[PDB]
Length: 92
Image (cartoon, rainbow, N blue to C red; front, side):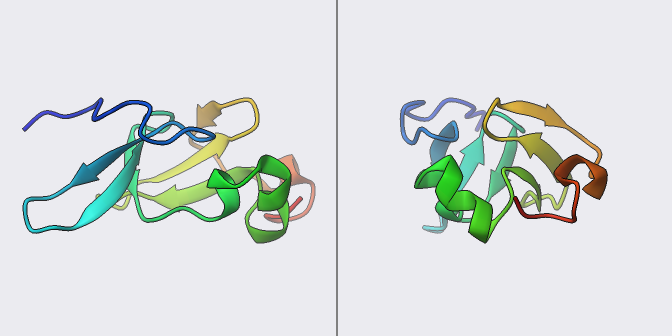
């Protein structure tokens, strides 16, 4: 099954469509990184709420375990995680 747009407006503030496997496991797919990921932190809350939890520039692994690094505020996506970007390590 080829799903890349289940609902689409399933969740915003971080473009994610709700996906579940026939076994009843539901995960989130973020079209930004094109990855499938677990229930996200304060990203679904508000960008400034995230900063204490997880930096707006973030690195996570998909269900395939691919790490992606993305600028959440501006919604740019890359693969490269220099702490130089955060100018620290991984928190705003």
